[PDB]
Image (cartoon, rainbow, N blue to C red):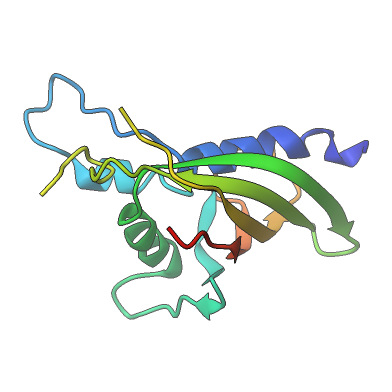
Length: 159
């Protein structure tokens, strides 16, 4: 409870970064995909170990794992996560803690992508999600602190 007093706000910030709504400044006449996409999961380290639905992201000569994740996540419809439970522990001697959390997430069914393009979000059915993070100790930092992320749907609706 005591060392995990900074834990809940950190998790909410991490999830907000996945749920980020794209807003184009009126000073910019064109969409800036890079400036939006690089904010998704921004607490990830460039060289973090990332696994999505059992499939590890493998670093390539041109794109590190964080970048590949951001490009993957960018292709989802807008999301809305609700944190429902968590637990965390420091791993003695490592300067890291492990955190497991569960959430529900739903996605925009409007047909628009995250830049608002086709071809008011309308939320679909709840998915279940489990996430395991290994994160540097100083979690009220907002920089690159996540060493590993395992993100997994534990329930996927048929519809």
